[PDB]
Image (spheres, coloured by chain):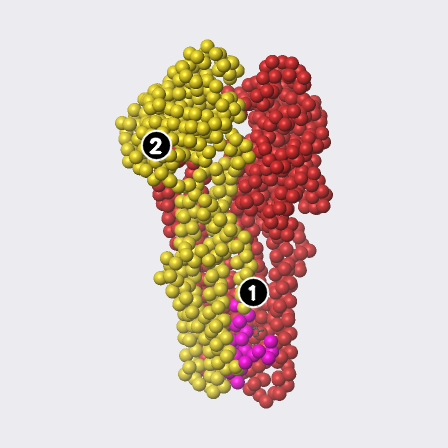
Chain colours: A yellow, B red
Amino acid sequence: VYLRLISYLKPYWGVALLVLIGFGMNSATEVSVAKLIKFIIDAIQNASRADLDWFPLLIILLVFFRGLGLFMGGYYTAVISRSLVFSIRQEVYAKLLRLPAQYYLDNSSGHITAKIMYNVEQLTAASSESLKTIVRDGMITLGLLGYLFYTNWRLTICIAGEFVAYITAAGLLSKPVKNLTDVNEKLQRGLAAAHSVFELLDLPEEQNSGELKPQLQGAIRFDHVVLNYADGTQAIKDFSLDIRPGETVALVGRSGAGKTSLVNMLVRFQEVSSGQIYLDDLPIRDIELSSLRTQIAMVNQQVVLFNRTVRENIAYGQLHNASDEDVIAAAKAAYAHDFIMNLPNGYDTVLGAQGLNLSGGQRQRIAIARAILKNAPILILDEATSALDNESEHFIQQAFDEAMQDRTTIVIAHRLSTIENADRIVVMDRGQIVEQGTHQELLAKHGAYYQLHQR
Amino acid sequence: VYLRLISYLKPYWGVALLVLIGFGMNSATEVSVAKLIKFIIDAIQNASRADLDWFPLLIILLVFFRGLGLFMGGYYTAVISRSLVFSIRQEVYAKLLRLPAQYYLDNSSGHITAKIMYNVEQLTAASSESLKTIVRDGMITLGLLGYLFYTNWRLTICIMVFLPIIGILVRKASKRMRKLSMQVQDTMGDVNHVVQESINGNAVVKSFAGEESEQERFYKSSEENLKRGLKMVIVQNLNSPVVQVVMACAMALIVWLALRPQILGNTTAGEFVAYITAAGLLSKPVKNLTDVNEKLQRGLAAAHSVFELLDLPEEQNSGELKPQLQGAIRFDHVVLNYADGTQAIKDFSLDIRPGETVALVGRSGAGKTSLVNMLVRFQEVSSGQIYLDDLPIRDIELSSLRTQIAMVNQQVVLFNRTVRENIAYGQLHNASDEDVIAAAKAAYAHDFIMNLPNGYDTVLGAQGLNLSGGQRQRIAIARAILKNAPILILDEATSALDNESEHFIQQAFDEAMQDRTTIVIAHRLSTIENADRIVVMDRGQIVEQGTHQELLAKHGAYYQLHQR
Ligand SMILES: O=C(Nc1sc2c(c1C(=O)O)CCCC2)c1ccc(Cl)cc1
Ligand SMILES: O=C(Nc1sc2c(c1C(=O)O)CCCC2)c1ccc(Cl)cc1
């Protein structure tokens, strides 16, 4: 699988010609050591005083050239290694963002952060070390073998100062050739990790089949929403979900319902392959992933706040449109300004300490404030998992109602009172909808009354 | 770090003496190379003819000794490094459990365990390479320098002048490298946290956001890390050449007056060549000895693993006793209040019978699962005494209390190594492989592991193997069975409702339920039906426990049974 690794280095053939020069000069020095040792024998035998006294300059020059070659070769191998690991890390992160997010369910965050970081370092370290040692090995072996073949010709039968030079140049093969038989160890160690990252380097991908920029419709119509849980069994049976613009409809489901799974289909998450979502001649890929994500803003019950400055969390989805007046209006709309402004100054709160500054209620209020400030054409409200009782429970409920009244919203039945206050209520049990129309008919039938009393 | 690391191979006194001899005899041969070339020069200069017979035998014997010494030394240092790393892994595995409730609860051990294992493996590689290099190169350098002293004692200016400057230069370089490694580690932590909080926050980034902002933030952090690393490796790859040049300059200087005219070393012409050669033999080993500085000091700096266990309090387990199989972990009038939050369980006196199946019925995220998991030091529980088997649980040691209890969690029990190491017990010698395999054969997960690759003949536990949630849950169940703990806690929500091995999983669970007491929280109707006795708790408090017939008779419990 190492073949594709060369493509990531193909940017760097301009600098890869310097490491060859460096290790070539290193090999030249490690061959010329034999030249020097042969030189001294003849100098002593013939008592050639001039070069004999000149010898220390030869030693210093040889070691300096060896050092320069090793320095530049090693540094440029390091540059290749670091730039390669940076490029691989950036590309794998870019792809890992796009993936359809079912990978996130079964694969925990710990495994992903272990992979994307340690695995790539292991791969690049093994590859760089193997390449460095194989280049050094090959070039020194070529130089020394040429030096041997220059004098004593053949050596296959076994397998004055000139004799000394030959035996030295033959002995020098010892450590390089020992590296030769050891490269495969590092290569296989790198192989053990390469498949883990390179397989994820493609690992399928989510795309924008519709490829339509315009998505300011505000109307959603879903027909026969049937999804099979990992192709083993249907999560929810067929149901018709037609939502008119502006109007808000409340959805109530029994135990085992898709709930967040059903809503996520409307947000281009876990797209329903078995479905008939067609509104105003728009297919399942109505506009695009980015367009459908921007036009519809959800309020997740999990409520996750990034460990960054409050400036970053205030305008995550609207970076250019970051306005102080808009942020103030959002803080007024949802009763969260007091919680943010109590501990820090407020303009730049800089949330930190692993979220210890703000409690869970303040975090939920901040999430609701961000959802309100999104002001998307369509919103999905889901707060069932949140605690019913809170210090600012009434304020949070009022903020949620104000956000729902802004545009079209389909509730996830966070509270029984909220569902009752909703004008339109639709109930689907086990994937089958038995309640429809005005809430007066449902109240008269009392079908949802028992569920509300139980919950 | 060195002081504590030394005490980890010190008890292995027997294996220590048998690794040094190989590198010592290697150094002896390497030194004898100079004596050999001294032999050759005077053999060629004079009319000696027996050299034609001496030389091949001497070369063959030297090669044989070098090969034998290197092989023996490498194998023995490999086994020593492996044993040391196994000891580190055993110590961290024992001490991973019971490090405060907040530390385990907040991080959920999903990333902490991975970070710890990564640090341990980095220390593994660094220690192995550094130890091999330091021992071999030190022995060869000391032996060769001893030869230098023996050959010409009066030549001592090489020790003088330059060598202290070389030493202080090396120390300064090491200090500067540590300074750069500090910033490298800082950027490492920053980018790690950015990536982790991006992973946990995919819902927000896809709901109302664009990936480009997060991509730019990650790009900035990664480029800063790149620049710091390039500066660090500038320092690294520049350290060795300059020290090589300065020491070689010192050697040339001492040779110059050692080769001064009208002395010529009394015109020996054989000893001087041997000395020059032996001095040249220093080049590569000393270069390796300088280069190992980076690896060793990077390992030391990354050795925060040796510090994580050094900082841990344990005061509750002051009973100085281990009840082992208590048989009943019960709490009377147990009420625990979270910090800056309402109490999850109030006026709860739940008790666990010996060997009786117990389950918790409640909504997702309710207090039932929290109360069930509260047995293993989930909360301080300062208010409200809890006594198990008519004795407070603080008497038992924290390690003993944790080990005696068993929990089912695929994420927590997931070793990033081969499946054989995945079911590794407390001790290597305590648990025989054959018995563990036979016991785990009841779980019927042996076929699932064997179908993908071969854990016995090849490394297992890859991404594909870990992606199977059912396989991971079955492996954890098998490990718990091999533990033979008195109390077992399991979650049926993680397990797939419908699967090919669902019937086998249900049969294995039914078989295991009779063996030992289970307080497993069951989210599946199959386990509820298999449960003879069920505990129903509302808002963290259980009014009473009734049988299946009693639950069916009561309308409120019948509705819950019909729902799930
Ligand atoms: O003669 C040998 N090796 C030499 S001679 C010399 C040097 C070396 C070396 O170890 O690189 C270093 C530079 C100065 C002169 C040798 C001969 C036979 C074997 Cl079976 C192994 C080694
Ligand atoms: O003595 C050293 N280097 C020499 S002197 C010499 C030679 C070499 C060599 O590079 O092998 C080759 C044969 C002729 C004379 C030396 C000593 C200490 C260090 Cl830290 C590094 C190098």
Q: Position of residue B140 (x, y in %)?
A: 57, 66
Magenta-tinted stretch: A154-176
**Amino acid under disc 2:** Asp
Mark 1, secondary structure of its residue: loop
Residue A168 is covered by the magenta coloring = yes
Q: Residue at the spot x=64%, y=16% of the render? A: B552
List the single residue furthest toward the bottom. B47
Q: Position of residue A450 (x, y in %)?
A: 51, 14
- Which is more toward the observer, B470 or A388? B470
- Which is more toward the observer, B294 or B272? B294
Q: Residues within 10 Å of mark 2 (few under 14, many from 20)?
A: few
Q: Which residue is mark 1?
A: A181
Q: Position of residue B26 (x, y in %)?
A: 61, 67
Which sits earlier in the primary sequence, circle 1 or circle 2? 1
Q: Which residue is mark 2?
A: A281
Labels 1, 2: front one = 2
Q: Chain of mark 1?
A: A
Q: Which mark is residue B247?
A: none
Q: Residue at the spot x=36%, y=29% of the render? A: A279
Q: Chain of mark 2?
A: A
Judge from the rendering whether residue A152 lies leftward or rightward of residue B86; answer left or right: left
**Amino acid under disc 1:** Thr
Q: Residue at the spot x=51%, y=63% of the render? A: B288
List the single residue furthest toward the top. A444
The reply to whether residue B309 is in sight is: no
- Which is more toward the observer, A85 or A101? A101
Q: Are marks 1 and 2 on the same chain?
A: yes
Mark 2, secondary structure of its residue: loop
